[PDB]
Length: 125
Length: 10
Image (tube, rainbow over all chains, first blue to last red; front, side, top):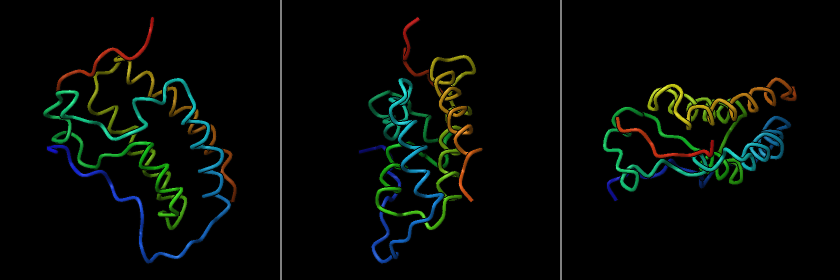
């Protein structure tokens, strides 16, 4: 495929280690966002070939999506919660730098981001 | 780059 390979989602030799914050990120934050009615454009990598977006991956240096984040959480890929939070932030940034302000997708991202940030403001210690 | 398609129902 002419799309980039998807981001890595498992680390073969990394120990399995939970934290309160990582449990929250999976079981509260990702759970809530995945089921939101506006989640679907964000549930998988952007398929720029299928969407005929030849400049998407020129504009977006660090692709990220909730499908990747979900797998990373399930596979205990993240060493800490901040890494996961950064991936969410990157996902939203990508949407806002590529898509025109006021496009449907942007309003959808804004609703998801608001919900995300409301949950992060209640992150455990 | 090119706009994405229609995504919500108004």
